[PDB]
View 1 (cartoon, rainbow over the protein chains, first blue to last red):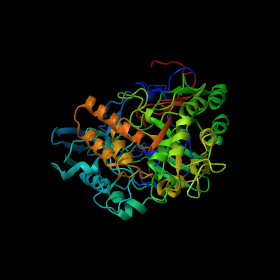
View 2 (cartoon, rainbow over the protein chains, first blue to last red):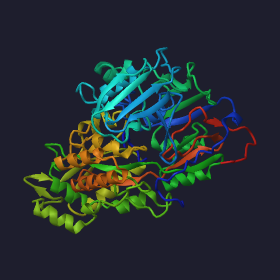
View 3 (tube, each protein chain N blue to C red):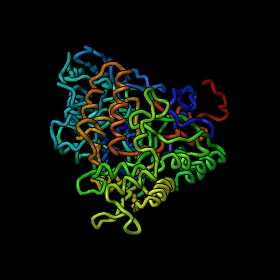
View 4 (cartoon, each protein chain N blue to C red):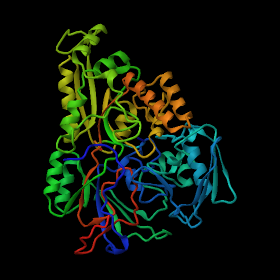
Length: 9
Length: 534
């Protein structure tokens, strides 16, 4: 889990 | 509709011989926002959407397959060798034809500079993750400028992920100094080395264009370009229907229905290791600094209902994600969520024992109301998550104040700085699940936005990374997960369905799951190309 995203992937 | 939300061993990409595809074309995709920083190693540039775009442009040392297996990408490295197993020594030998887009060759200095920049030695680098760089004792020059030998001071099983998967190699000009690392990529990306190159950043048109890298020494891509358009979540499916973009994710049942109804669109499905969650803030001065309050509140959030509402009709027998380290379908996955199993009556009891009593419309203590700011990225699905949690928490006397936000600064201006009590967002994993431990859950983890941790969690992470046996390492990681749940760090909700809507004309592109794309192979099929040999 290294990068993030604002929306549910 | 019928497959489970679990990581498997396949991709769904409409594989075709790229030589039989059209020569040319413009792959049109969407972005949520222009990033505030294009350095994907930076704390403000750790955006999965941008990292996904950069994979078409930057070297990665390994190709990951649909089962998570790795092979050396010989476009970038002649060879990569575990020169010595313990102490670990890895020798990267760079493909002599590899050049950055400014003419500079790729050399051992790029590997040394990057490892130093994310090692934590110099606090001026504002990094998102170390990817184990703090465990390398040295990076030295091998037999010539094109060879780097990386010597580890401690075991690190997932060394292949340093420059692969979500990791990738940046040029020393962008990593050598804190100034360049932190501020050199604010307006756009630095030099790159891949089949494509970012050639246009139009802030007015809200567009980013990738075209063929002239210096690319590998297979000539079939595509002329990849174009990214900024679009909000509600605009994505209409854009696909109107023929303005060519692929976009499918996150709800109604989205799946619209996409599947649309002529010329295919539904591809390959779940990857990514998930959505509530992350709690335990920083001093925050209301959730109290661990017992975190665990009580957690007992009032119904993750199972949330997962069923989020995923019904989209996946089979929807369930919530019950692990921080492994997701469903991965080796080592297990349910460690029981310490905070949904129990409103028990939540109420624990809230009373703490002095959060029903003194008013919501519970109160020492003149403060029990209100929890929920920071999330405004969209239909995310608002739904927030609303369900709001309803169940209201039923136990807890007020969830929804704070929906937007724009490029959701992380850099809110999440990264602790501007929340709970924050909803997603983590996007790859084939290297252990590398998240030091990043997110260690007490000094660079992505520990909520500053929640303990010496026991730190020691359990240490034991996990010291372990050379994979099965024992998975056991130790699950003990870490148990401690993470018991600390009220975060509540995993749903892992990705892996459903993507793609223009039916596209080949070697779709739902990849664990696998990398071969960006030289993406292309559009010719007319009456209706055979499927894969």
